[PDB]
Amino acid sequence: SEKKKIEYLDKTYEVTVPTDKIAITGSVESMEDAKLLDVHPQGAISFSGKFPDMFKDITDKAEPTGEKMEPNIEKILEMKPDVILASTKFPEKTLQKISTAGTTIPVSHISSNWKENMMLLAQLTGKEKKAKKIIADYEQDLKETKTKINDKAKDSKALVIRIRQGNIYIYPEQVYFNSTLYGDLGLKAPNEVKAAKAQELISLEKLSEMNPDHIFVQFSDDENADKPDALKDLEKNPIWKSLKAVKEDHVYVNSVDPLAQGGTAWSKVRFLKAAAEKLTQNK
Amino acid sequence: SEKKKIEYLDKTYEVTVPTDKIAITGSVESMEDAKLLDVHPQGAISFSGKFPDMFKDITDKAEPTGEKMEPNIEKILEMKPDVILASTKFPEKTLQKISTAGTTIPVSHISSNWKENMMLLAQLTGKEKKAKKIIADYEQDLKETKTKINDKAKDSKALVIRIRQGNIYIYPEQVYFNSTLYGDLGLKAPNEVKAAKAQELISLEKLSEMNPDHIFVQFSDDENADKPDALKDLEKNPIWKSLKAVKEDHVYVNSVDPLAQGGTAWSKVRFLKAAAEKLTQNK
Ligand SMILES: [Cl-]
Ligand SMILES: [Cl-]
Ligand SMILES: [Cl-]
Ligand SMILES: [Cl-]
Ligand SMILES: [Cl-]
Ligand SMILES: [Cl-]
C-alpha cells in the first residue's frame, strides 16, 4: 500500500491503497457496495445496535461506527482507519468532526452516482477489475432485459411500495428501486411518484385509483415490529383484492431483501434480476 | 381442472389439477418449492405466528395452517383445499387426522428427494416445464461449477455451521447444505459431520481442531433473539481469529438467506451460486 490519489465526484483525496482499514459511517450505500465487491471493512454501521443479517457477510471483521446518522467518533478514532467513508447526508460540521479521526470521503446517497460509489470502493480495495465487470454485466443485462420485455409490459403501470410502521409509502422517480424501474428499464413513472419529493404515504384508495399492472411490495419485519400483521391486513382488504395487479397475480412481495437500500449497485443488480423474471414476455 | 393421478415416491394420489387450493402444513420444503416455482398457496405454515419475510413472496394469498409441527385442522378444514401438502415428519395418526380435511400428500423432508418434491408441486400447478428447466439448469450449473473448481479446492476442508440460540451446530452429511457441499460438489465431509446423526453442537475448540479451509456460517437474528451478539462474540474470540479460514478470508456468513432449509431445490440453487462464487479458481 502506497498513498494514492483518488478522484471522487470531482474532488481529490489521498488514501493509503489498497486497504481493508475502512470505516463506514452514515453511508449504507457503501455497505451495499461492500456486499457486492466482497469487501470486509474494519468499521460498519450499526442498525439499532446490531449488524443486520443482510450485512453479516461483510461485517465479519467489523466493529460498529455508530448508528447510521450518529457517527461514533470515539469508536472511529479507536480503529485508526486509513479511510472513512462517510455520507453526503452529513452536515459539513459533522464531516469536519469525522475528519479529525482520519481521511474522510463523503459518499453520495444519490442513486445516479451508483457507479461512482462502487468505483470509489473498488479503487480503495484494488478491486477495479471486479467492479468494472459488475458494471459491464449490469449494462449488458439491462439492455438484454429491455429487449425481452415486450412493448405492452414497457407501457404498463408499475409501482414500488414499501410498508414501514404499517403504512404504505411510495418514493420519488429517482429514488429507491424507482431509478431501476423507471430510469433504467424505461417504464413510465405514475404522476404520484413524479409528484413525490421524498418517501410519501399513500392510501389504499389512491393505490386503487392508480390500479397498477405490477406492484413490487417491500416489507421488512424489522421495520414493522409494532404492526407485524400490516401486510396481511392489507392483503385481506376487499379493495386490495379488487386491484388489477392482485387479480392478475402481479404483486411481488420481497423480490429483493426488504432491507435493501434500493438505489445502490447491489440493489439495482438484484432488482434487475427480479424485474426481468416478472416483466419479461414469458412472464 | 380435472382429477389427475399423481405418482409421488411410489404412492398414487388423485388430485384436482392444476390448482391453487393448496394448503401446506409441516412441509417447509414445499414452501421453498413454492418459492422457486412462483406458486402462491392458499394455506401456508406460520412461524411464531408470522409468515417470515423470506416467504412473504408466496404467502400473499395464504392464510396460516398452523405452526410447522402443529397443523391447525380447523384452519385447514376452513380452506377446503384441493390438496394438503403435509410432511413425512408427521406421525401416521396426525396424517390421518389431516386427511379428514382433504386429500393429503406427506412430502418428504429428505434432501435426496428434492427433485421429486419440486416435481410434485409442479404437477399440482401445471408447472412441469418450469420445474424441469430448473432441475436441468441446476444439473448443468453443478457440472460447470465442478469443472471450474480446481483440484485443490475440491480437496479442501469445507464446513457449514449454523448458529442458533448462540450455539454453533453442524449437520449430518446428507442434511442441510451438506447435501450440496459434499454430495453434489464432491468435497469430502469431515469426520465430525459423518458422525453427526442430527443437528449437533460443536465447540470452538473442535472447530479449531478441524481448522477448515472454508466455513459457511448461517446466522438468523430470528433464531438468536436472546443472544444477538453471539456471532460477534465468536468473531472476536482469539481462537476464532487463529482459524485458517478466518486468516484466509474464507468465512462466508449468510451466503444464503439464513432461514433457508438447506436441502430443498431453492436452497440448493442458492447454495450452488454461493459456493460457485467462493470456491471457484478465480476465487
Ligand atoms: Cl456488533
Ligand atoms: Cl437478465
Ligand atoms: Cl404476512
Ligand atoms: Cl398471518
Ligand atoms: Cl455456476
Ligand atoms: Cl453481528
Image (cartoon, coloured by chain):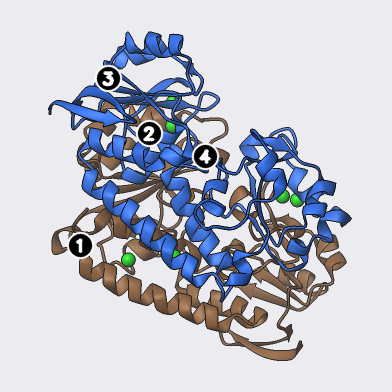
Chain colours: A blue, B brown
For disc 4, the chain is A
Mark 1 vs mark 2: in front: 2
Please state, as top left, top right, bottom left or bottom right, where the N terminus of chain B lies in the image.
bottom right
Front in this rendered view, residue A217 or B275:
A217
Answer yes or no: disc 2 within 8 Å of ligand 6: yes
User: Residue tagged by mark 2?
Assistant: A59
Relative to A77, A218 lies left or right: right
Q: Tell me the mark number nearer the camera, choosing from 4 and 2.
A: 4
Residue A3: x, y in percent? 14, 24
Q: Determine contact: label 1, label 3, CB under 8 Å.
A: no
Q: Helix, strand, or loop for circle 3? A: loop
Q: Is mark 1 within 8 Å of ligand 5?
A: no
* Left or right of B278, for residue B81: right
Residues at circles 4 and 3 in contact by the CB criterion of under 8 Å: no
Residue tagged by mark 3? A81
Q: Which mark is residue B275?
A: none
The residue type indicated by label 3 comes to Pro
Q: Alpha carbon of mark 1 to alpha carbon of mark 2: how far?
A: 27 Å
- Residue at image mark 4: A261
Q: How far apart in space, not on screen, are marks 1 and 3 (Cα)?
A: 37 Å
In space, the residues marked 4 and 1 are separated at their CA atoms by: 36 Å
> Of residues A110 and B57, which is closer to you in this image?
A110
Same-chain check, marks 1 and 3: no
Q: Position of residue A188 (x, y in %)?
A: 62, 55
* Residue at x-position 34% and y-position 51%: A135
Question: Which residue: 63% across, 71% down?
Answer: A152
Secondary element under disc 4, as helix, strand or loop, is loop
- N-terminal-most mark, 4 or 3: 3
- The amino acid type of the residue labelled 2 equals Thr
Relative height, residue B28 to residue B166 (above, below): below
User: Residue B90 location, x and y as percent?
Assistant: 66, 66
Q: Residues within 10 Å of mark 4 (few under 14, many from 20)?
A: many
